Amino acid sequence: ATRDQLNIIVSYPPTKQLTYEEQDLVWKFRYYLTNQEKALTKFLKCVNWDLPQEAKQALELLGKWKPMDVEDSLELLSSHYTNPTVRRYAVARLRQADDEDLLMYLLQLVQALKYENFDDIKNGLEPNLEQDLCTFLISRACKNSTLANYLYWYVIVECEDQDTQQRDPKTHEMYLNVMRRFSQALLKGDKSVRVMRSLLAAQQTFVDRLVHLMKAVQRESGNRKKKNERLQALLGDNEKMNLSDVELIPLPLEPQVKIRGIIPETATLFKSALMPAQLFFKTEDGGKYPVIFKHGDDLRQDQLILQIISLMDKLLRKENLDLKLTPYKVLATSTKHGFMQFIQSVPVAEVLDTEGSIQNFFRKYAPSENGPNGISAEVMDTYVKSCAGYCVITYILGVGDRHLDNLLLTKTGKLFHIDFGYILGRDPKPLPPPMKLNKEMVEGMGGTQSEQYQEFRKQCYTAFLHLRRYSNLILNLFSLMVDANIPDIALEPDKTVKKVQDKFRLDLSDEEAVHYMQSLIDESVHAL
Ligand SMILES: [Cl-]
Ligand SMILES: [Cl-]
Ligand SMILES: [Cl-]
Ligand SMILES: [Cl-]
Ligand SMILES: [K+]
Ligand SMILES: [K+]
Ligand SMILES: [K+]
């Protein structure tokens, strides 16, 4: 009875509002819940922090409480929590995460600095619970150069944000101070952390030079061939432009990769409105890392989606489920330019135009006499899995504007999506289908009577059930994004988390969730 009503409350997603009745029920049993880590955030929610005596008692219980997971602590950094001791406790729990996990949350943690104390951040500038979020991140960045790289670029983009600057100067000034504190901590560090500062400086001037080059190509008119030759000439002039021969600097898009420079003679522009450049970076070890450099575009919505897809890919792998996804790197180097990792691939629309069908494509580049449908069993297994993975992930994220030009394919059988300009349920058309599945994908795996389609359906159920188990973490991260300058979030900041929460159907048992996902696929198929 009373015990059952608590377990329902405790198991709520982190963003659901407890009723008055629910809050006072949680309070009454506060002492009966101290060994349930998943109930601590529910308790903290129901505390009148206004009242000193109750706040005292609440902090006592926070001390005696079974410590909460790192994933749940992310909730305490959101805008709904202002008590300093609660926010310092969140940081203390975050300290238990290793750097691989921390890096996967970094984009959101940088947004959460909006919810920190701005005076503390400023006051740390030279003219257990002892660390706020800013001090924590700078401290972790000074020990890991990959963390430092992303901290720098994440904060630098929030600094240049002209909407924030005009519309919320206090928050813009905080991010300047965050960057000033970072620089200060780097200069006070040992030779290791001190050289990191100049590596960051070298990356920044390289991007400025690249930005300047893109503009130079576009100064006068010319056709694409003429513009490529301008691009190539300017890149090869290293005295002038200095982009083809640099001292092994980290690549911002992926700082583990050290770059000697851009290869001048293989750089070209894409045929599109913004004419982003395809650029091959020379690696310290003689290899090539292809990127797209975009100028005149805000990559931050793409950056968020690819960060989330990367996270979901890792969660699934943690569960021994590798769906062959393609979480390509995206890094905004400004609100107006950025990098994307280039993946060798071909749009499905071009597959249909040239080979007539996904199956024909596979039979041309990966045949197998005894393989399924004459296709390499290895390639077919890669295609079924990546279809299942992307069907579930784009459903959960409500990605829209899906067509055969932003569905991409590799000769190894990987299918993946690109261009996430429409998310969280926005779409150019009204009444879009909930499962982003089409007739070309289903024919690609042999149609709906095939063993592959069965496998695809099962991989969809598995993926959905696993990601459901991580709904708290995923909902928490999204709740740190509700004030970000990301267009599809800023449209309805107060409905964003709910939009993602609903997709998990946390109201269904696992048994029921699998039936639902089965009907989602069949109904989408029946409609195709
Ligand atoms: Cl009520
Ligand atoms: Cl009181
Ligand atoms: Cl590590
Ligand atoms: Cl704080
Ligand atoms: K990352
Ligand atoms: K660095
Ligand atoms: K990849």
Image (cartoon, rainbow, N blue to C red):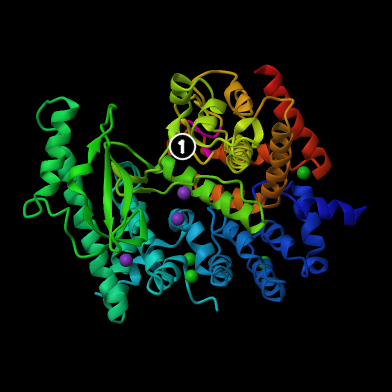
**Residue 264 horizontal side relative to residue 528, left or right:** left
Magenta stretch: dominant secondary structure: loop
Q: Residue furthest front?
A: 369
**Residue 277 horizontal side relative to residue 227, left or right:** right
User: Where in the figure is residue 327, as x and y percent of width and height?
Assistant: 49, 47
Give the answer, above or below, for where 413 lies relative to 238: above
Task: State yes or no: residue 94 in magenta.
Answer: no
SS label for mark 1: helix
Q: Looking at this view, is 76 or 509 the one in front?
A: 509
Q: Looking at this view, is 482 or 526 the one in front?
A: 526
Q: Residue furthest bottom?
A: 190
Mark 1: few, some, or many residues within 10 Å (few <14, many ≥20)?
some
Write down the region rendered in magenta: 414-424
Asked whether the viewer can see residue 305, the reply is yes
Ligand 1's image quarter is top right
**Residue 444 horizontal side relative to residue 401, left or right:** right
Which residue is drawn at the image coordinates 36% and 53% (left, top)? 171
> Which image quadrant is residue 10 in?
bottom right
Q: Residue furthest left?
A: 239
**Residue 409 horizontal side relative to residue 63, left or right:** left
User: Where in the figure is residue 435, as x and y percent of width and height?
Assistant: 64, 29
What residue is shown with label 1? 490
Which residue is drawn at the image coordinates 35% and 58% (left, top)? 174
Label 1 CB less than 8 angstroms from ligand 5: no
Q: Looking at this view, is 377 or 147 the one in front?
A: 377
Task: State yes or no: residue 422 in magenta.
Answer: yes
Amino acid type of the residue that numbered disc 1 sits on in the rendered structure: Ala
Asked whether the viewer can see residue 49, the reply is no
Which residue is drawn at the image coordinates 82% and 38% (left, top)? 512
Q: Looking at this view, is 67 or 509 the one in front?
A: 509
User: Where in the figure is residue 86, as x and y percent of width and height?
Assistant: 58, 66
